[PDB]
Picture 1: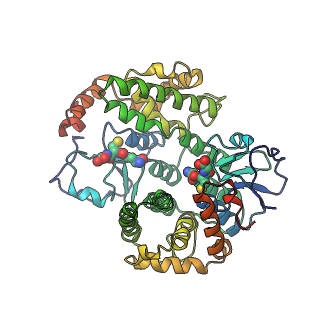
Picture 2: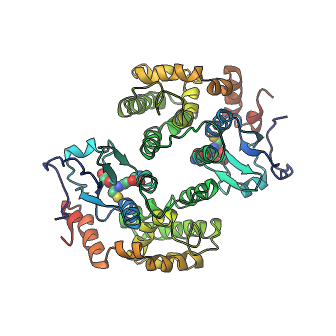
Length: 236
Length: 236
Ligand SMILES: N[C@@H](CCC(=O)N[C@@H](CS)C(=O)NCC(=O)O)C(=O)O
Ligand SMILES: N[C@@H](CCC(=O)N[C@@H](CS)C(=O)NCC(=O)O)C(=O)O
């Protein structure tokens, strides 16, 4: 019963000792960031999915912005903005550190994130565009932005922060996952490193574990395009 | 000779052992963030101002975005985006920590920063607006955003991160400094805490030390509005 909560739903009880809770939506790439970090760190947690068309009134008490993801810990603290939530999880929980100890590498990873920053909007505006015109230009935009990542980051290692997967990879992944799902892999045909990086990413056990199937993505997508409240719950 | 560097200028030499260098502009509030942190931490540094109308070609090698601020350390590393530069300085240098040790407080400070995020654009669009219409609406916008900071942050202490000044205060200050300079203090007449916070901010030795005088701001502003390359160098 991972079915989303909507208007009229009971405000949830307090997050139990030993857990953290994520307010999420199954097809939200921003929330995927958080879930990737949760999984990679082996963090014990609860998921509550939020129906984004039919939002529970109590949800604006969780995040004044009314967006997912939001973390709520067992001390009743609330954290929103996907990047903030990922950084918090890495700092507050034991195990493999996803952010490097070194201040420059940390900074460089945030600089990479900033290079990637145009992509999410391009992806949303693609899904939500129906004119032959806007496809052509959006494609050009994809090319431009992907070369930025390819050329400006000057990756020499398998992943964006070095030889092992780390925060920066998990931060950008969801939109590359979506790119594939949208059959847009050819947008990275001119960017050899980025292209290889995608293949390496899919071999990662955490990335692998959180991939959404073609079936489920398409199911969400259909209902999303019909502006249906049931889109969030596709595939059950 | 803090005169800005422009097209044709010699690319600067390597940053000397024992120093960090900031690529700046005297009337840039984003760069003010960095300079505030430099001062608060007592960090030994160089300033090189960049003429933003007449940019040195070599400057895009410092930051592909061609924006200030940029840090360059004596190991030849480059850091851009004001927030990234401030966080790096705090991590990489000794003394008073401006960010709290605790992961939640860190996160909360970033959440505050996100609440403030609409303000810089509103300020720029005010300076650069000449229609009676756009003043009225921009004023409304100011009110709206300031109540967000007032109401959503629910400050109970003198500063945004507690009883002492810290990163979050220095991050948002430049635009409140600019608000005053633009004679817009009345935009915070409905926000008592924010209003008191401004007074407390001006008592801080670092904030105090970096205030730009009414004279100099107006001098920059006049020439900025004439789209003059000499705007950066006003007051000598
Ligand atoms: N900047 C936010 C964006 C989060 C976001 O946009 N989430 C979407 C779903 S992917 C949302 O909650 N939308 C509901 C709405 O917009 O009303 C983040 O990084 O977390
Ligand atoms: N997001 C950037 C914005 C920096 C920025 O906009 N700086 C301006 C001056 S305040 C700039 O360099 N403008 C030159 C230009 O736009 O061409 C930051 O946080 O550092």
